[PDB]
Length: 101
Image (cartoon, rainbow, N blue to C red; front, side, top):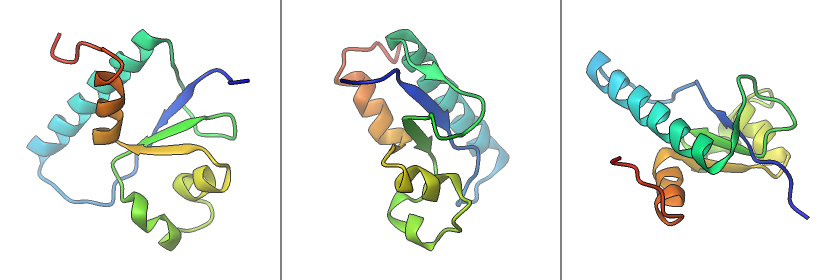
């Protein structure tokens, strides 16, 4: 049987951008956060072993190059789901969630 959905938003980046784009990414984040709250996900402040999903802006295909203490390493070690913002926004759409609204 399944367990409560607990989502951690990775706060670390592996990309550079200007201030404008940061704000735009932060909006995307909050907007996504708001969507998952709606479906009833729990949105945890800290990362730990009870997270079921990490939503990250960083490079998933390159996790193998990360330190062992990096939350993305740990998430993969722990068979958690790691999603990009795109895949996440897909998840919400396909589940009939008004993103625009």
